[PDB]
Amino acid sequence: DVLGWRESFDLLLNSKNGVAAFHAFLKTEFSEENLEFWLACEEFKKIRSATKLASRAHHIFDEYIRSEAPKEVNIDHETRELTKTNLQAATTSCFDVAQGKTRTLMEKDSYPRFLKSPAYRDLA
């Protein structure tokens, strides 16, 4: 299980202990919103009902995407505008670009540092 976390970021994100450990690592450097947003996108795509999709999409946008949002993720204006536009036309891949940018924010920086920290090394 712990081996999978370094073989694939996707395996780490599907692990109960992995996610908990990584969330704590991120919280100490004020970037846990990246992980919370990613996970929120994953549950969003499982929604079938049009009404729930609309409601959840608006909450996700207001909580993580719009300027000055409580847990605003570090995305450029280009992506924020794109997401809003997608929100305007109700598309299921509404958050794809934002999720991918946020994923890279983790995968190419905090993820590798997490693996080289006691939080991961002690569990290996």
Image (cartoon, rainbow, N blue to C red):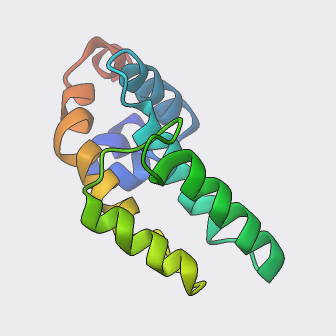
Instruction: Classify the position of the N terminus by image quarter.
Output: top left
Viewer-closest of 64 and 23: 64
Quadrant position of residue 5: top left
Quadrant position of residue 3: top left
**Percent position of residue 92, x then y:** 57, 81
Residue 122 seen from this side:
yes
**Percent position of residue 51, x then y:** 82, 76
Residue at 37% x, 15% y: name it: 28
Q: In this view, does 66 lie to the left or right of 117?
A: right
Viewer-closest of 124 and 22: 22
Is residue 23 placed above or below 93 in the rendered structure?
A: above
Viewer-closest of 9 and 58: 58
Q: In this view, does 11 lie to the left or right of 47?
A: left
**Percent position of residue 71, x then y:** 49, 37
Is residue 91 placed above or below 45 in the rendered structure?
A: below
Residue at 58% x, 36% y: name it: 16
Residue at 28% x, 60% y: name it: 77
Residue at 26% x, 67% y: name it: 78
Quadrant position of residue 68: top left
Is residue 109 placed above or below 97 in the rendered structure?
A: above
Residue 49 seen from this side:
no
Q: Is residue 41 left or right of residue 109?
A: right
**Percent position of residue 7, x then y:** 27, 49
Viewer-closest of 86 and 120: 86
Instruction: Classify the position of the C terminus by image quarter.
Output: top left
